[PDB]
Image (cartoon, grey):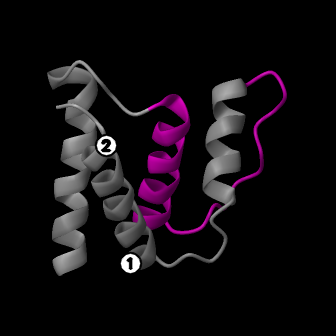
Amino acid sequence: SMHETRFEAAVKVIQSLPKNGSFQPTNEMMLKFYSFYKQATEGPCKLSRPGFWDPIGRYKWDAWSSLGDMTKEEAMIAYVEEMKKIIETMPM
């Protein structure tokens, strides 16, 4: 599908920024990207929240859980739209 192809292209773009540029998305933005990636591929968050002692686990889970019943296609659209917005503002 058009959205699935766009999604794969976008994922590649984001993956490449910490490797091929001098600038990358913020940690906050990376968690947002993770949330849409999970929602697009695995669907809605299923598991219980990690414990207080696992910060990155908790930040991850909170971001993914936040999306609720977002569909897989909506999460692909969201990921792509977020990537476009970052690329529009960020020196490459």
Asked if residue 39 lies left or right of residue 44, the reply is left
| Marking on residue 89 | 2
- Which of the numbered marks, if any, corresponds to residue 73? 1
Q: Which class describes the residues within 10 Å of circle 2: few (<14), some (14-19), or many (20+)?
A: few
Residue 30 vs 35, above or below: the answer is: above
Q: State if disc 1 and disc 2 touch (CB < 8 Å).
A: no
Q: Which mark is residue 13?
A: none
Q: Residue at x 35, y 63 (%)?
A: 81
Quadrant position of the N terminus in the picture: bottom left
Give, as a single range, the part of the protein colored magenta: 26-54
Say which residue appears at 77% left-offset and 51% top-offset: 48
Q: Quadrant of residue 25?
A: top left
Q: Nearer the viewer, mark 2 or mark 1?
A: 2
Q: Nearer the viewer, residue 87 or 70?
A: 87
Q: Position of residue 51 (x, y in %)?
A: 82, 32
Q: Is residue 45 left or right of residue 18?
A: right
Q: How many marks?
A: 2
Q: Residue at x 39, y 56 (%)?
A: 82
Give the structural element (helix, strand or loop) at label 1. Answer: helix
Q: Is residue 3 a member of the stretch shown in magenta?
A: no
Left/right placement of residue 23 relative to residue 63 reads: left
Residue type pointed to by label 2:
Thr
In the picture, the quarter occupied by the C terminus is top left
Residue 66 pos. (x, y %)? 69, 60
Specify the amino acid type for callout 1: Glu
Where residue 83 sits in the image (x, y, percent)? 32, 52
